[PDB]
Amino acid sequence: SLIESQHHHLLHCLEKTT
Amino acid sequence: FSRIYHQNQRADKRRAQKKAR
Amino acid sequence: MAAGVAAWLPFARAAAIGWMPVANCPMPLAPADKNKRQDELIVLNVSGRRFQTWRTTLERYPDTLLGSTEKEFFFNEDTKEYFFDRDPEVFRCVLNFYRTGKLHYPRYECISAYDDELAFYGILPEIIGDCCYEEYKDRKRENAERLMLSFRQTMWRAFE
Amino acid sequence: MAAGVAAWLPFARAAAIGWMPVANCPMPLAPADKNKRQDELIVLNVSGRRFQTWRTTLERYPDTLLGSTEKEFFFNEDTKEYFFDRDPEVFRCVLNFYRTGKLHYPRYECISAYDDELAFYGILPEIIGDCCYEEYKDRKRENAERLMLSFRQTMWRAFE
Amino acid sequence: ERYPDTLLGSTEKEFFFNEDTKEYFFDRDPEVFRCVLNFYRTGKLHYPRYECISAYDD
Amino acid sequence: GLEQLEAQTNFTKRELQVLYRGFKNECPSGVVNEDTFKQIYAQFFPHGDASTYAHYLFNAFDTTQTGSVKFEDFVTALSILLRGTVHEKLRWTFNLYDINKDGYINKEEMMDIVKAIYDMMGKYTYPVLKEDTPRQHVDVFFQKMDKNKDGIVTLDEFLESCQEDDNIMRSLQLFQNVM
Amino acid sequence: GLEQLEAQTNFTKRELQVLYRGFKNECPSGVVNEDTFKQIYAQFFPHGDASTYAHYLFNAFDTTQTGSVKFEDFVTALSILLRGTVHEKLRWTFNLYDINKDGYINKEEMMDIVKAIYDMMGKYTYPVLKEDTPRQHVDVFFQKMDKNKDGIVTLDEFLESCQEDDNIMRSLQLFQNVM
Amino acid sequence: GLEQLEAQTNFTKRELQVLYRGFKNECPSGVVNEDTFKQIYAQFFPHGDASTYAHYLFNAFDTTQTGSVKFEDFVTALSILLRGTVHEKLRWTFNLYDINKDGYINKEEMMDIVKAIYDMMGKYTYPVLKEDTPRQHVDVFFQKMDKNKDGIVTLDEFLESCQEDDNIMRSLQLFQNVM
């Protein structure tokens, strides 16, 4: 898909709340 | 009323014009 | 950088920075780089007429004909231009939508041709910009209207 | 392989396979193969306006100018183009017809020019696709409307 | 260069000028650019009766 | 897809686009269905009814249980029927005659089809028409195609009986040359 | 000018034109403001509200004192934020955390930004939500970016203890070569 | 058939294309009729009658016996009339004069032609006008064109008398050069 990669990556790097 | 009268008129008119084919 | 559907990701890659120092979390995710190449003005030949646009502008909606990848049934490598034997003037609206992302209606179009070209290129006649919507339905309904035993039932048929 | 008028004949040649098993025939007729050649974009030069179309599209109606071969008088062999000293707009109508096989009528055309170009292409105004037909008749009737002794009858002259 | 207070009037056109072909290529509609060009010709602008005024305005 | 099918067919890329053109011309890539066969196959049959026959080979074409499957599903079968092998062309026409879709054809099973053919013929047969011939036109099948003499033909029992009449293999392959 | 913007930023000509295209595609290059970021910055972050954070990096973004700065000042900082050097990203984040626009920040001020982060994280936290750790995640932040224990951060004091956070070190410039 | 027309006419492909253009332009390539000549010859010869002799060379151009044939037989006769052979040109001019369709000309028969051309001449002649000169302008015909002095000239008898007059032999070839 090569688009869900980038968009999901931002929300992944978001998930870093503790 | 006028709208519907023209409607039926053009209706049977198109019917006959189609029957021409 | 990126365009088409990723026309505003750079602002996101700028704004992500503001959480990096405060990222007291152990490890975020590294980026998703890959092979790279720039866009190109793909050139369409519709019945002798020529249009051009970036490929990402095409890829914006792959649920269409050109938006998808199967435009190659009409790609003439002999020309390197996807040639189509349909009208370009109605295709002009399609291109313009591909650019903007909204479609409109040339008022003077025999609605049959407009609709069947829409279908031809895989477009949805419902997502027309409502700024020009009801007149489409009016053309629809007017065109719809425009296109509109031995003895027992013998007397019957004779009556009506 | 072939297209245009014989664009779906391959489907019939596929369907004909179902006969052979039960076909108790000793020997049917050998196939009717003949000279074949792939189609190309014949270019129509209408007042510099450049159009391109497959011969297959061009030959769906050989009872007209384009389908018949008396189109070469406008064919500028110097350019491989059929140059036409006519309207670059009403031509589009005939062309999108040949694509479809049905005729449309734009709302805002001088019906005089319309019918004269139709006759010029040999096409019959009677065969207009009912997609938009009756309004053509309205333009017809309106245009028709708008385009409309010494002493023993000099008395008559003075009367009226 | 009759009015430098526009996209083409000012020098912001090379952002779409293609030195790769020595042309200003623009991803716009060909049936509205003509009206703007006609303005640049005269200095006034007409408006065709059949345009989805949204497209015109934008 | 263009190349995902090119890697499956017996035609070239231009021979594929030349049919994609005519297909998308009449059908806006929805999918060709019975509604298309019962007209285009019928419009080719004046003095004859094509629907009674098209009804069978539509679902014979459709490997899926759908009523409008795919253009890919159309061309993959066109490749077999035109430029395929006799062994698979006969498998396809058996699946056609196997109206029950099981692999076992009965006398009346393909009588239902020879009637469709005789109906597609025309209003009146040009020689004398006897409705026992579409009955016995199936017998001439089984007496050669029913090796078990039982009255029901299966796959191999029809194949091993459909490869000796040289004229039919001469006839199955007349159309793999047209282009 | 086009060249006048090239020699200022680190990006190239193709990148700059292909980005000004998308820039104008949503706003007619009038000038970008709050309301357009609150939808661009949100359109990539579902399950959350990204307006409250964009509300800070927009004023830190605006080199002028207006409510909407420019496209030229847009790229002059887009460069620093994507391919710019680490220590300049730190100074600009310093301009961002300092809501009072002075260079002096107290607990609740930057806690209001860590809220925005952890607010747009989502409506329901996927692990258990604890609202006092926004008191402590800034508290545990203090002990790093402060060597005086007074309650204020200045640029040097606020940076002299993130320069060695290797995770944020390799993570702060992830997009300096990816185009 | 343009190529089959070249095998009959003496104009070339460009001379044929550019003239068929003008042909098809003024009339929608239906057929040329009497009425059309009755006006296009009226514009090229005003201030006088344009029908009486027009309906003579129309039926002369009319090879068959209908009222309107086609474009091809029109240019194949243009070839004979402009760049055609003299022995065929005089035969064609006699078939023009041959009103009664039989092959024999009476004095009053060509009087019908001269009373048409002098009518076309206009209202008042530059010299004096007399209805008796059309009576001698045909008789000065026979004295040279009627070798038998009977009052009837035949194709052979019109030809044997129309090869030695040099000035008409120059007049009949006036337009095989102009293009």
Image (cartoon, coloured by chain):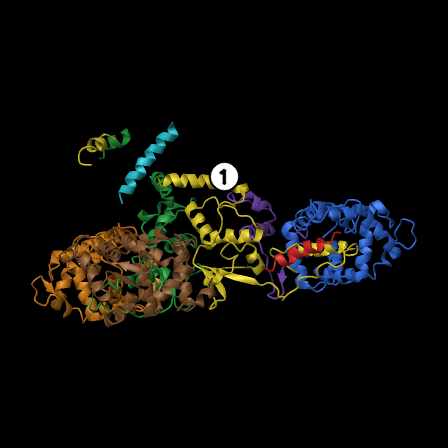
Chain colours: A red, B cyan, C yellow, D green, E purple, F brown, G blue, H orange
Is G49 or C98 nearer to us in this picture?
G49
Res. G11 image quadrant? bottom right
Judge from the rendering whether residue D38 lies leftward or rightward of residue G53; answer left or right: left
Please provide percent x and percent y for residue D106.
42, 46
E10 lies above or below E45: below
Please provide percent x and percent y for residue C53.
56, 59
Q: Inspect this view and state whether residue D26 appears.
A: yes
Chain of the residue displaying label 1: C
Judge from the rendering whether residue C136 lies leftward or rightward of residue F84; answer left or right: right
Please provide percent x and percent y for residue F140.
20, 63
Q: Which residue is mark 1?
A: C134
Is E37 or D28 nearer to us in this picture?
D28
Is G131 or F158 nearer to us in this picture?
F158
Q: Tag 1: Cα neighbours inside 10 Å, few (<14), some, or many (≥20)?
A: few
H117 lies above or below D149: below
Please provide percent x and percent y for residue F3.
47, 66
Res. H152 image quadrant? bottom left
Count of marks overlaid on the render: 1
Q: Looking at numbered disc 1 in the image, what kind of residue is underneath it?
A: Glu
Quadrant that contains the C terminus of chain G: bottom right
Local secondary structure at mark 1: helix
Q: Inspect this view and state whether residue H44 appears.
A: no
Q: Residue at x 11, y 62 (%)?
A: H103
